Image (tube, coloured by chain):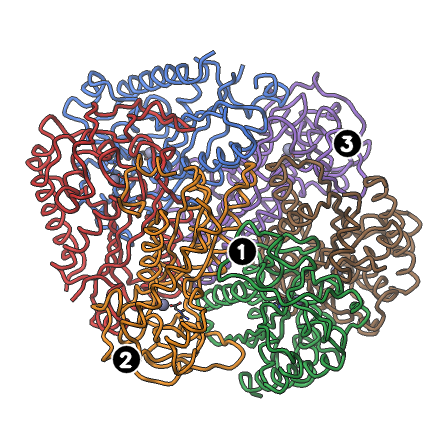
Chain colours: A red, B orange, C green, D brown, E purple, F blue
Amino acid sequence: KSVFVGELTWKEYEARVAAGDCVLMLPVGALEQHGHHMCMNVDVLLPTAVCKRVAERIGALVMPGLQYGYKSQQKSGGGNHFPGTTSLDGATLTGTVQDIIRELARHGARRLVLMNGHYQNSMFIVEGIDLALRELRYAGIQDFKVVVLSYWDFVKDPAVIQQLYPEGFLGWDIEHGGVFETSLMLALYPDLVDLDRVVDHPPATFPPYDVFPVDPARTPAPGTLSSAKTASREKGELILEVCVQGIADAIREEFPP
Amino acid sequence: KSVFVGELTWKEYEARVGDCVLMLPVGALEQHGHHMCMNVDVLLPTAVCKRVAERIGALVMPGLQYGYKSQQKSGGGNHFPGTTSLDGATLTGTVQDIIRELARHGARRLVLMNGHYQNSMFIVEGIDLALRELRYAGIQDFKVVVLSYWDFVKDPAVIQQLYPEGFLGWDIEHGGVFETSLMLALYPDLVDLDRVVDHPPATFPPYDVFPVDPARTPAPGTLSSAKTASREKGELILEVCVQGIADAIREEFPP
Amino acid sequence: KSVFVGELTWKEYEARVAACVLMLPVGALEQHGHHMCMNVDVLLPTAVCKRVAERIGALVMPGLQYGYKSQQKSGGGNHFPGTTSLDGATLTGTVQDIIRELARHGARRLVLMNGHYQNSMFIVEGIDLALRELRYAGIQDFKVVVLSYWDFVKDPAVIQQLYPEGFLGWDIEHGGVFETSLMLALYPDLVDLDRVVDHPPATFPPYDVFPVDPARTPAPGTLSSAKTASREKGELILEVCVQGIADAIREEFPP
Amino acid sequence: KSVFVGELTWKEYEARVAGDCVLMLPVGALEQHGHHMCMNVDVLLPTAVCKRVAERIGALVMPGLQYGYKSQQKSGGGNHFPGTTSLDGATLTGTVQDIIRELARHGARRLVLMNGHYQNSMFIVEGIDLALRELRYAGIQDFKVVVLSYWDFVKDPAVIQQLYPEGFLGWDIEHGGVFETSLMLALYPDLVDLDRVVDHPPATFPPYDVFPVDPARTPAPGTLSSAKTASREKGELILEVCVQGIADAIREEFPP
Amino acid sequence: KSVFVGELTWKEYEARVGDCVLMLPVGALEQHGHHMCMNVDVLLPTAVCKRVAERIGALVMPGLQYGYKSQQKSGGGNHFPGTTSLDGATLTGTVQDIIRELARHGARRLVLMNGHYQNSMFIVEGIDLALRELRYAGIQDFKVVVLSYWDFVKDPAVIQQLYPEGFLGWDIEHGGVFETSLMLALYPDLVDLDRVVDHPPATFPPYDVFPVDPARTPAPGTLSSAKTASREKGELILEVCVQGIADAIREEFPP
Amino acid sequence: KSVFVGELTWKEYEARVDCVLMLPVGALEQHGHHMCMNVDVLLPTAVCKRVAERIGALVMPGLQYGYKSQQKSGGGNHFPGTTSLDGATLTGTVQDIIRELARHGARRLVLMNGHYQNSMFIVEGIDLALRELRYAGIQDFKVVVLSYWDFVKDPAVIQQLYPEGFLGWDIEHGGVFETSLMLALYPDLVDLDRVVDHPPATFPPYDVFPVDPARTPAPGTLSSAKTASREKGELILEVCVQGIADAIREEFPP
Ligand SMILES: CN(CC(=O)O)C(=N)N
Ligand SMILES: CN(CC(=O)O)C(=N)N
Ligand SMILES: CN(CC(=O)O)C(=N)N
Ligand SMILES: CN(CC(=O)O)C(=N)N
Ligand SMILES: CN(CC(=O)O)C(=N)N
Ligand SMILES: [Zn+2]
Ligand SMILES: [Zn+2]
Ligand SMILES: [Zn+2]
Ligand SMILES: [Zn+2]
Ligand SMILES: [Zn+2]
Ligand SMILES: [Zn+2]
């Protein structure tokens, strides 16, 4: 049977929550430029694919993903001045998370994993969680538990990091449209990637501060913050397994049967 | 190439963009009876948008997956499990933000295709607030067309062919013949006609009660029976909607 | 003794709740053609509430004078002069605040009577948000009945009596026979039939366009002609509504 | 012709705005006013004043705001009383803001906000600021607003002396007292039963406020001062002073 | 030991906390004439809080540095340079958030000491919204005392001594004798009496005008002259306020 | 003369407004058993003052309350003393201030963050304020936002401060960095003898809500300030002031 809530009938969903201990997962992405070689829905596709595989392994269900996320920031996404990128205001994203949690609680669900796939979403997801739990408390509900994470943070093994960045890891912030995402895309959605279009520029570097209005000149022209020239399907499969295994284990730990 | 903005690179999108027509599916995650899945309201308008876009050369934005609270007289009620609804302000704000961004891109033509009966007024408010802000910047050439795809099935000949026993009304076409037929034609694996509870059409008094009373809604959640739903009826509906909408867009947004 | 809360002392009000059904008219300030005034949507539901209240022993709260933005397909459009509309959040918040306060008073029975086509969904959101908060306080016995008074005019005989040429739908009724007849029966001085522009019923394609385009609406602002309106029709309408609503409320809020 | 916008057709309204016309908006509340008076006093009075002022200067009157901000103990008894139905600050502010936006859309550029409920002031002010801020975004800076509480125009020592023989008590503790009750006796006598007035000493409070509001610190009737000496005659005197004073003020601020 | 929460470790704070009295000064950054600095509204109530706290054994929270928009009739107007004001919703939300957090700590007694004439109603709304929320959580023992420190200078003998030439009124005491005298007593370096513009007390008609007309405000921004301001007057004002507030707090929050 | 806007008369402020304005953004947060709770306001404010004196800028009254403390970088908002604002509140505060500064005619602002959790909300406040200015055709209001500790990155300086290795800014809550600065600037507000010497805090690659107190070192600190010193504080201070003064001069030149 499908692990996606949207593909279930309400009766099937009800039974799964009734069984108690049901774990729900919600992918949180964005519509953002990802250079000259990749499509713009990468941040939705990746966490969703990871969620699906984790759900298949641990018997969890996956909710429809959030398609639009917070404003792209220069130092970690090129900047919200790029065409295509379609961003939400913080209050909008926070409210969306808040509403969904409120509804899931109404269903009787008490276990949620929010899987972030867009660098800028984190703090607003966090505020959404806090405001939702605050309200649940008003209604005498304190047994709703949430696990929030950005899937790339699970790639911690020095051996894996070295396979991806033999010359040194430069941080998840400048990874935008680079080796990590491009490899995953090559393994999962190769038709949406054209490696021949990658602009092999040097890793983006910035001073210890931020400037607004965002200055287009301080970002590499392509929109990428690092080159995906060395990306490969094999690296993508490595990343995928590492993330899926790591997240599946973490969820089993936090939400035992 | 793809008609979906999400599958394009930013350079491809940029090239396509104020002459390009953008389309945004607006659905919901809502119970649709014992015989159908819950993401129907996203799947259907998205499928219609895709076909319309292919025919007129438009682009489709990622659809809104969650919509306004289900209302009893037209959706069974928001008390059902699975249905995951947003507050009005949240939905309104989402539409407002997207229009602001599309305008920033240079786009000036948007079609909002609603697939969930309860969304309409919040989409309207989102549109108004967005246009209000554009006006603050001296921009008044952004044009929006909003519609619920089922409204394009209006031709008497078509209505009779689809409903030889009589039309029931869009309000109670929740998990009924219309949606189920479309699903049988587009996503048959998500429908199990054998699970359809063949009850008579739902009727209600001329008022609403809150908190919602579950007893006033058919147990299955549907408001009319899909027993006579068929793949053929779905194909007709699809063709009518796609042609009608394609024509309307060409009219409002000449190439 | 008055049925209006505003005309009672707080002691009299307190006594009545200690014993009660509260009614709240929700209208708007909207253009209503060349022949009628602009506070029609407040006047009418208020007049119905008053009569219903007198019959069932209920109390009427001060009405909401401003409603949601006028929409073209059911009100001509918010581009007209005079029409003074609130944002959705504003109307929703107003309904929410009032319910909270009535609950504080100890009231637990409310009938929201809408008289403006565009208010419905925002009244609904206001109710939901208010009930959500009451739940936070452990209060779950507050019941709300919401309705648009025209929905109670369903009898075919009555309908034919009113629309000899066929029912046009409550949406295109704006400033037509129905409202004008009621105004002739209740506030004749605010109507001048000689000024009625007798144009054919407004028609629109199966979609909406924004910014609202003035040319898609009949110049007068009305969506249908009130040429055949009369005090006679008004009295018929009034009795049907008052009786139907009185019975409905008695059923939902039994003694 | 009526001075009330609600009773005009949109064509008549349009002609009147076609930005020289002065619009007036009464802002009241639904609040307890003792054992002797009804609860819609704060809407009735400023509306009656607007009507008479409008007739003299040729202005138009908008439908009044029926609900105002939460009643405060020191000037209204407290929001804990039954009947009083109050809005949150944001709601009232947003209402004023929405209305100004629309009036500006009509082409109107002159507005008089007449407050009749003590607690509304600051929220009306914020609504005005937010509305003018938005108009400025569109390059509009010729929309002018005059806001006032009608009782502030009653400053004449002679008039004041008749109403408050032992001295002016302040517009804050006037709640449900001689001033409002007299105006009501002159305008809507059937809504007042002077025999039910509870003649208590003017309410006094320490130089601070306490929340949750303590009911025991407010006179039981809900009034802050006694209306025992209220009279139709006093009401007529007040009415003429206000109408005249406000009519003159508006003519000066919004010259023909 | 310090009476300022900010100077304590969380353990020391925890030890002190629901019998402890917390104090929160609420000021603003506002123009105060040619002779005085702009943070007067923060400095003064904080200095009073410090002294009251030392006497009664209370703790003082970090003060609110920005307040509501300056109003002409009581502050000259928000059109002046330097004055940096918050929207009402912002100030209300800040007060609301802080109370919610203090309650979480276990605190149940709070004194909000206002020092800016315009803050009052927004502080009041913040308190109400916070208490409303606490009630949802089943908490009804949180008590709040709110006051503008200058209101405690009311004794006829004191006003007489401070104003042998007549009291002018708190509304026009902006950058006048009262504040300037307190500053001369507490922060003399931030005052330069030689720069005082000795103009007549500001007077206004019984109404308000927006956009604010700068011509209706004395050019220096003050509403009354501080020419006769003195350190002695400030010392008296301080002693009177500290004693009066300390006694009031002991009464409302007995040990 | 003072570099603080609050200590100027409006005439003096008006005359000064190429002027660079600086706004410290802190918080009231628990900082272990050995240090006070207003550290996040005191430090950025101290740095702003020194930078301002050196480059001729002015300093606005600081934001005293910041966003909710997060476990992985601040121990958690479940601690006593910590008094946090909701995101919308902090965002609206920044937004309102920028609106007003622009009204004054100011066009150069430096927001100096001193609390780890504030960043994204400060960013949103900036965007919303710039959005409104754009409605008026204004595009010359420029904002530089930074967390002062990010200027301590010179390998030679890091080696001096952390001869045994840098732990990361996320766990530098009440640790060597902040404690050293406090020892150099406000020694009376620090008592090293109260430092609880526990190993650096570590967490899995995810967060859990409701926050679980058990996953945070009991003291509230995320790293030990045992080796904190006044000497280290003076070095950090000089590095930050010099680096920030240069960056501001670069972004806001004569
Ligand atoms: C981790 N990522 C991915 C993304 O948000 O595109 C960064 N841009 N840093
Ligand atoms: C047309 N529909 C479908 C839907 O909104 O789910 C109705 N429920 N009436
Ligand atoms: C029922 N009505 C009346 C109105 O709201 O004006 C319609 N315009 N449809
Ligand atoms: C009491 N005050 C001081 C102030 O708010 O600045 C007046 N300006 N009236
Ligand atoms: C660097 N900081 C500062 C703070 O917010 O205490 C960390 N918490 N890590
Ligand atoms: Zn990405
Ligand atoms: Zn559906
Ligand atoms: Zn009508
Ligand atoms: Zn009154
Ligand atoms: Zn002051
Ligand atoms: Zn810190």
Which label sits on residue E216?
A: 3
Query: Residue at the top extreme?
Result: F254
Q: Is residue C40 above or below residue F234?
A: below
Residues at badges 1 and 2 in contact (C-beta under 8 Å)? no
Q: Of tags 2 and 3, which is closer to the observer? A: 2
- Same chain, marks 2 and 3? no
Q: In this view, does C105 lie above or below D94?
A: below
Q: Mark 1 points at which residue?
A: C89
User: Seen in the image, is F225 located left or right of residue E108?
Assistant: left
**What kind of residue is marked 2?**
Val
The quarter of the image holding the N terminus of chain E is top left
- Same chain, marks 1 and 2? no
* Residue E243 horizontal/vertical position (percent): 62, 41
**Secondary structure of the residue carrying numbered label 1:** helix
**Secondary structure of the residue carrying numbered label 3:** helix
Which label sits on residue B196?
A: 2
| Quarter location, residue C136 | bottom left
The chain carrying label 2 is B
Q: How far apart are marks 1 and 2 (CA)?
A: 39 Å
* Residue E192 horizontal/vertical position (percent): 66, 18
Is residue B132 visible to the viewer in this orientation of the structure?
yes
Which of the pair B123/A140 is nearer the observer?
Answer: B123
